[PDB]
Amino acid sequence: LSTLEAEMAVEKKAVEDQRDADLEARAQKLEADLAELEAEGAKSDVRRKVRDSGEREMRQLRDRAQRELDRLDEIWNTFTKLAPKQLIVDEVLYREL
Image (tube, rainbow, N blue to C red; front, side):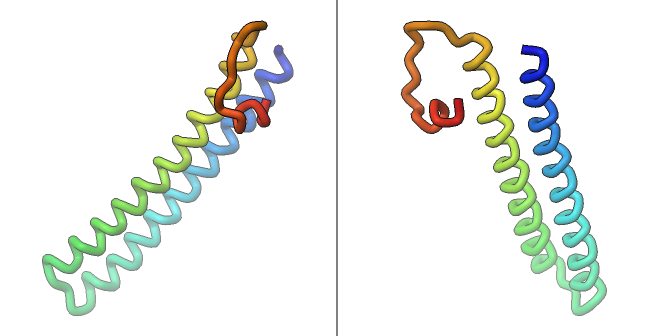
């Protein structure tokens, strides 16, 4: 249980580091690309539509990564608390186990 808990946290951390690296890069792309639009023929409403599409895209990026974290925690919890008579209806989670 010690070695597996470690590996599981390392793998779970690798997803956290990957998420933080992508959201920062996407945010930088927003700053740089939004600066071009604000410095060149800028208008109030259009820039808001570009940043809204930027915020919405960033939201989806964090949601996806959080889904994997939720899936990972669902996998580690099921193994530690596992016992006979337990029923697994996911079938993809069972394949992962």
